[PDB]
Image (cartoon, coloured by chain):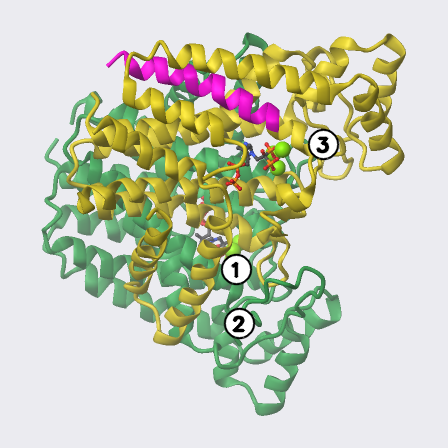
Chain colours: A green, B yellow
Amino acid sequence: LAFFRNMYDKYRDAFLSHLNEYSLEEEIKEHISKYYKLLFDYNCLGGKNNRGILVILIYEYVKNRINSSEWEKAACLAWCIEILQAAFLVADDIMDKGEMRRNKYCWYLLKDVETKNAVNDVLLLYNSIYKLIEIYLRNESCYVDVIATFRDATLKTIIGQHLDTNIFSDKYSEIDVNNINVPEQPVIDINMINFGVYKNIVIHKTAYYSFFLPIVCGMLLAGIAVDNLIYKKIEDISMLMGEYFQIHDDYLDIFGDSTKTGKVGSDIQNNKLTWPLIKTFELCSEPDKIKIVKNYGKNNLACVKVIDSLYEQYKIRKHYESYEKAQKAKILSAINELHHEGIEYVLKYLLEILFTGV
Amino acid sequence: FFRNMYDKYRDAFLSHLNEYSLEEEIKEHISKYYKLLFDYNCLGGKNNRGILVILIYEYVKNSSEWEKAACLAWCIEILQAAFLVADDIMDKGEMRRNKYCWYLLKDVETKNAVNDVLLLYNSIYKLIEIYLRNESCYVDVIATFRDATLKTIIGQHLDTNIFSDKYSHREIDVNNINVPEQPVIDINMINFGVYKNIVIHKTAYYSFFLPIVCGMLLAGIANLIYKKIEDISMLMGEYFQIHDDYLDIFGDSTKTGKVGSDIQNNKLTWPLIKTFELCSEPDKIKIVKNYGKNNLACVKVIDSLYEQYKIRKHYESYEKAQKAKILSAINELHHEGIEYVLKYLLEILFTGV
Ligand SMILES: O=P(O)(O)C(O)(Cn1ccnc1)P(=O)(O)O
Ligand SMILES: O=P(O)(O)C(O)(Cn1ccnc1)P(=O)(O)O
Ligand SMILES: C=C(C)CCOP(=O)(O)OP(=O)(O)O
Ligand SMILES: C=C(C)CCOP(=O)(O)OP(=O)(O)O
Ligand SMILES: [Mg+2]
Ligand SMILES: [Mg+2]
Ligand SMILES: [Mg+2]
Ligand SMILES: [Mg+2]
Ligand SMILES: [Mg+2]
Ligand SMILES: [Mg+2]
């Protein structure tokens, strides 16, 4: 764990090093190294580090101890999930018109960067992962399985980000290849406001890259055979934990303190299908439905305020806290079926520090 | 038969998505969206890169072997697609292959397009796994796509930032979200050394080195010929990009499929550098004053300078001398089969087929 924290530089600088081998003029090489050193630092640091720490812990509690060449490979994988997070979050804030990420301006918003650099930079962060895994793990037998898990995790996430972004779109509620002029007015689709659709999305956008991937990396490296039925159990727990983590997130979009969360709430105005939106539709009077249809998805104070107060009226904070309690018990029940005492402690521990880090 | 086989790889990938734990109506929605993403962006081009895989493979060496080569061939066409979607966002593109750029469609927008670039990119590796996973060259193939992709990313970064304030002692300003940069050229960067740097990275690696290498690995070449091919590919990428820069100024968008944008986007182009080489100090001053401005009278001045200094002429002469340098490099390959394909690629490069 202190190996992880202290070895950020190592992996950052191993990748910067690879590009310094490019056939470029020395001045150009210097400019690239400055730009890219910032892109990693700005975008990979400042968070809780829960995914990376998970890789480290799973790895340790699966093995009976671990040399520093072994740690160097696990912390590699751990940082690569933290680079994956970076890439995803850079793109998310473009998609969601983010203002603040980890208490600092979103990367795409910087005048030195903009959306043109940010898009190129997502691709860079994402490909650095695979270069770093080649550097530290090409000779391991889990090597192909590790790179497969990253790419399949990433594909699931890309699908869920697509659904998060289009579930209410006109495309769905034939795509028009002739319209570049007539913008679509954000409206909610009431046929999509149920927990079934919500789960399809949050499992895909959150659960795979955030829980499944880092646990599987820890296990693949520690050497659990890919045909072991523990991986399926692990997948089922990841889905429970993923939906749990994402609901807490949706909850913070309205109830959090932007100085503590490090980001600014935007789901109402960005027309998202969130747990609060679904719970309220489940509970609210028929005229309040007409009221959510009218006011949701509008970057307008009085419109957002209507929604906030319907969430105040329908006691969404209380319904959340009773979801947290019921879902946590559900996760713990599944963890207790794992028949691996090492992984169980880790996942119990994770579940405690999930919202805070540590 | 290259193009016959397109649906096979697209639908193989769409089948992969269809296995996701998603409600049936949602799977239907995603099949429609993604089929269009692939059809819209993979189809319509010269397919030079895919064809080059196929041909290199044939000339280094049954229908199951062709299933693997066409797979790689279509994966480079998918990478072309990913890079172009991203490039048209970055370059404020208007048309690509005589249709509106994907990012502009009201049903897509930049928010979708950014995600879709990653979808396209990642689709490649799933396809190579489906078709080549038990090939001994599997890991070498995925490493080649990956490294050529890193190279292209760096090159696109340089193309997009070479004249920028951050490069012109001081740091990226992490507190500036409000004061937009006023684009201006950096005269210190207007040289062919810097231009070859950008151009081998953003074009030559994925456009030449990658398709040729794909066919050579699969045909089973383990070998100092790889460095000779690298060197030719760089020669070819430069030649090809200089042609592209040429078309940006002198082309017809109904024939190029795309609307020229380099002057207003502040690109370090071959016509820029060739003009800077040959012009007077007061035209240098005109260039500084007018380049990188999305303004008619400004692009007009630059365009007028390109007429005045006979850039069309200088390009025709460049094309002649550089084709000759590529053929001289090709003749040093001492591989009859690869040599034939490259000579022929060189003949069809600007037109296709
Ligand atoms: O709410 P999102 O899904 O946009 C978010 O959680 C990011 N994200 C992206 C994928 N999964 C989660 P963030 O609120 O941090 O902006
Ligand atoms: O001039 P570009 O680099 O933008 C281009 O050639 C595309 N491209 C992208 C990378 N290398 C070349 P296009 O003129 O097609 O928009
Ligand atoms: C994936 C979700 C739900 C939000 C971002 O995740 P984290 O809260 O784990 O982000 P950092 O700790 O990395 O800032
Ligand atoms: C790498 C360059 C110069 C961009 C255009 O590529 P092509 O001219 O190969 O484009 P398509 O045939 O794929 O349309
Ligand atoms: Mg977001
Ligand atoms: Mg989002
Ligand atoms: Mg959120
Ligand atoms: Mg470009
Ligand atoms: Mg372009
Ligand atoms: Mg061009």
Q: Distance between the residues labelled 3 and 2?
A: 37 Å
Q: In this view, does A104 lie above or below B228?
A: below
Q: Is mark 2 on a helix, strand or loop?
A: loop
Q: Inspect the image, locate mark 1, and give the three-letter code of the amino acid beneath it.
A: Leu
Q: Inspect the image, locate mark 2, and give the three-letter code of the amino acid beneath it.
A: Glu
Disc 2 target residue: A174
Q: Is residue A218 visible?
A: no
Comparing labels 1 and 2, the label whose residue is closer to the camera: 2
Residue B239 is one of the magenta-drawn residues: yes
- Asked if disc 1 and disc 2 are in contact, CB closer than 8 Å, the reply is no
Residue in front for this viewpoint, B68 or B125: B68
Chain letter for mark 2: A
Crowd band around label 3 with a 10 angstrom C-alpha radius: few (<14), some (14–19), many (20+): some
The quadrant in which residue B244 appears is top right
- Does mark 2's beta carbon lie closer than 8 Å to ligand 4? no
Which residues are the magenta region?
A: B223-243
Same-chain check, marks 1 and 2:
yes
Q: In this view, does A24 lie above or below B114?
A: above
Mark sitting on residue A252? 1
